[PDB]
Image (cartoon, rainbow over all chains, first blue to last red; front, side, top):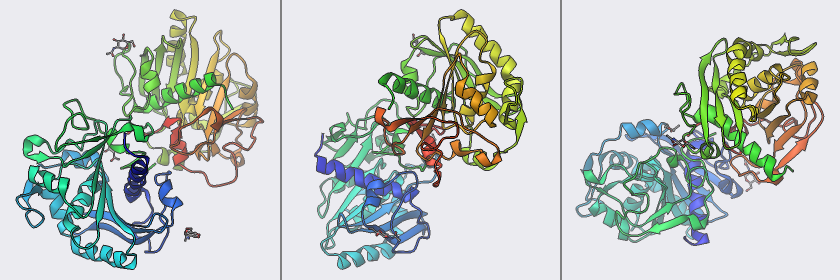
Length: 269
Length: 269
Ligand SMILES: *[C@@H]1O[C@H](CO)[C@@H](O)[C@H](O)[C@H]1NC(C)=O
Ligand SMILES: *[C@@H]1O[C@H](CO)[C@@H](O)[C@H](O)[C@H]1NC(C)=O
Ligand SMILES: CCOC(=O)CC(C)=O
């Protein structure tokens, strides 16, 4: 169990993550009103949420998402969509760690992700800062599903400590680095990271710990089944880097579980 | 609003339909249990249900589905899969009728449906009859979603009146023919036919009345949101051939609402 307020927060951002796939904005003009096909993001629509900046396949990592202004909830939101073929993306997924100490002393992160964000980070970091200035009392949030989960975490750890707090809600995001980094994201100030996992989902389990990867604490694990609705009594906050008894169990994984984070995600109807 | 019992029957066959897709049926040993991936058919798995005859691309219209024995609910189920790609299927839908007086007089049903069914009625009726025999007490039920529900209203009135009753549960099925044929199913006996519709489902709106098509009565219409759970109150009964109030209203049909009958259907996570 977690608070209702936190539950609402998790649901709302699982929907922002989702919109990264099912909103019709691949080229949509900044200013339009955010919407999704297949009831993928209702709480998002209900709100006065508009696009500020949309974006596709950006630079070296082929990165997509959008930057929104939510006047109802007073949010500046940056969303990272995941792969358009998550089953693939999973099979192609190397476990290569590149070092990154510009971010943190000794921290070893995934080569792939880190490389992709770093190659876009400026053109965007400016864009957030822009709105933070435009709306100083608005909370800045980054969110993402699967891959997009991985990114927003990175972009998160990488942009805080600059003036405004940056919150991060990742859904079924994979490991991003070594026990150093795990710790950096576990304690780091200037924001809070909400790492949400569903059941056995197969991504929060890769790359493996065998390969030097570790998971930051804590973990909000959704116990409810795939396709089952989520209540605040179905989430267990799991404490301690790489704790078990959450998503991280020795049991057999699943790929659908990935696509069910408080609703349909990583795919559009 | 339906009774709790009917609801359970609706949910059960909605899942047997999904199972025509998300099961790992293909051709697998007769006598093997039934299971679906992505929690597409929990209630079916929950039942002591096994395959009796699987078929992949049988005859003229590459007909696909399976014949199941359910000792828990005492059923002989014949589930008809819909198209492998429902967008391309809707798109290329051919609208030509063809007589089928040997089902009923002055009866013209969609050409390709009737023709695909026809090819198999002999290999199929033979399996049903075979199972009806061992399990005389068991209730025979035909079910399906989309092109699958269609093929099941047509093997429906064709194989009816032959000793055993045949119930038909259809999930967002298209019109299967001309009005002489509409009126028939509406009041044939030795088997009720529950035609089910979800909000603005695009498929039960084809072919259109314009091309000489009629929908039978009554209509069980789920009016709850796409990806919302269904309660007993979200189902409304709709009488009158080609009546309106359920799915057959004048507003934009949605393809997504076609994929949500109680549980994700016509697509597998
Ligand atoms: C944008 O949303 C507002 C409600 O917040 C609505 O009044 C307005 O008509 C919408 N405009 C567009 C283009 O969607
Ligand atoms: C299949 O289900 C039946 C009854 O539900 C059970 O007796 C049998 O052991 C099961 N077999 C497998 C492989 O699940
Ligand atoms: C098991 C296959 O699932 C997927 O890859 C889902 C998707 C469209 O991304």
